[PDB]
Length: 372
Ligand SMILES: [Mg+2]
Image (cartoon, rainbow, N blue to C red; front, top):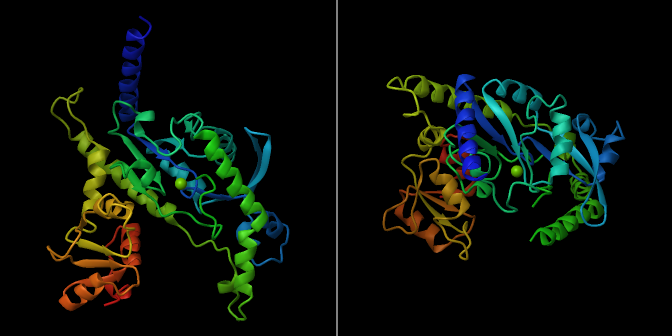
């Protein structure tokens, strides 16, 4: 019936796209919004600072855009302030040459459209390839299957959160973009989620966290103005992401093009295999033991930090049975720390050593994070 034929049609269409992409010599890139390529806030403090050229935060707010949104319930309206990550225009422009772009956000569709309107005014970058929490199919997680149910060999994902992707092998976790300091992700059981959301938005509009932190910084008599200014433009993560993305593409089409041995629907490259290969080298050789990092209520080997570290080739042990190379500790003289210190061959470092190493795709010198 109109289902057997339909499913066969959808399947043909899916393989068509995979073929189309390889003929354009491109891949698919799933792009997250919040804290990946933008940062948003409803803290009215932004509008106030933007209206005062003499304000210490004025200069870094010159490129900030805003828009209004009223949604679902009883027309709750909010003025959103959007800060685009440095170099975004060029990143999208350049990356579009190697990847077909898709947006996949946990924000609402209305939210996504407004953001898309600004970053993609001609609609050529993303077209209609935009997924929001209104049509993704989940309020807690993202799935490659929502976009590529049968073949994910050509899809790369860039997102600041690895948990919403189950630390999928196709994921390139990005350093969270936190321009509006102290503000996290304004977008994080539908009506039950909307409630707490509208609550976080209100708490932000009334508590003015930005003003609160800026005031605190100024209330500390000093001379170095810069260190007293809350907002700063010191992020060029996109230039780094561009490099990694160019490499993945290059490696994929190198393996792909050299699949010369009946290139029909025989065998092709797989970003899902290529990416892990690239990351596995970073912390290969490291055996990590955590102390005061993972809550006892949470499982260690399934914790986000552990999975993040393992995606980069590190091993995560639970005890000293097999002496770990590093003890990731949370500034607390625990029995694990004492133990490792007595062994003298274990590097006792702060969590930062690991998160910064993972963020830089490079095993950093323990010396700067060493506790023992
Ligand atoms: Mg995000």
